[PDB]
């Protein structure tokens, strides 16, 4: 259960179950590797865990988002996983807050802005 990778975490945040998020703390604190690193993001576009979480929402709920935010800012880079956007030429600049606005969900917009989110982000 200690072994962690992109596919497991993406599936977990897709389902939307917070009970499976336990364990990331120890793995990240033992590898001293931030989730914002290119390793945990898709190499082609640059999609991160939040984008995967928001693109699939069950009648406007995703309970994994908030715990993901705490495990973000508890140990993160000076721009913790909320100021990071896509890197491909086609979706360059596109951040998670743009997804939140596009999905017409004000709750996740509040969650993203209340934990720090650049409201400019020129896509």
Image (cartoon, rainbow, N blue to C red):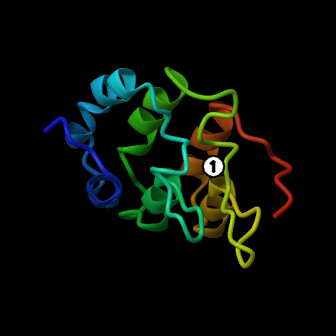
Residue nearest the observer in this picture, 54 or 4: 4
State the image coordinates of residue 93 (x, y, percent, origin top left).
76, 62
Quadrant that contains the N terminus? top left
State the image coordinates of residue 28 (x, y, percent, origin top left).
37, 29
Task: Tell me if 85 is positioned left or right of 32 in this view.
Answer: right
Residue nearest the observer in this picture, 44 or 17: 44
Taking the spot 70% from the left edge, 43% from the top edge, the residue there is 83
Taking the spot 81% from the left edge, 46% from the top edge, the residue there is 119
Give the image quarter of residue 27.
top left
Task: Tell me if 94 is positioned left or right of 77 in this view.
Answer: right
Please say if 1 is above or below 102.
above
Residue nearest the observer in this picture, 92 or 113: 92
Please say if 18 is above or below 42.
above
State the image coordinates of residue 50 (x, y, percent, origin top left).
50, 52
> Disc 1 marks which residue?
109
State the image coordinates of residue 106 (x, y, percent, origin top left).
61, 53
Taking the spot 27% from the left edge, 41% from the top edge, the residue there is 18
Residue sitting farthest toward the left: 1
Give the image quarter of residue 76.
top right
């Amino acid at each position: 259960p200690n072994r962690f990778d992109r596919d497991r975490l993406f599936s977990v945040v897709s389902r939307g179950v917070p009970e499976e998020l336990t364990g990331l703390l120890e793995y990240l604190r033992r590898t001293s590797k931030y989730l914002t690193d290119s390793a945990y993001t898709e190499g082609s576009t640059g999609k991160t865990c939040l984008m995967k979480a928001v693109l699939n929402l069950q009648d406007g709920v995703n309970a994994c988002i908030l715990p993901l935010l705490q495990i973000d800012r508890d140990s993160g880079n000076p721009q913790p996983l909320v100021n990071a956007q896509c890197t491909d030429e086609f979706y360059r600049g596109h951040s998670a807050l743009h997804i939140a606005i596009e999905k017409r969900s004000l709750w996740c917009v509040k969650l993203l802005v209340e934990n720090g989110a650049n409201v400019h982000i020129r896509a």
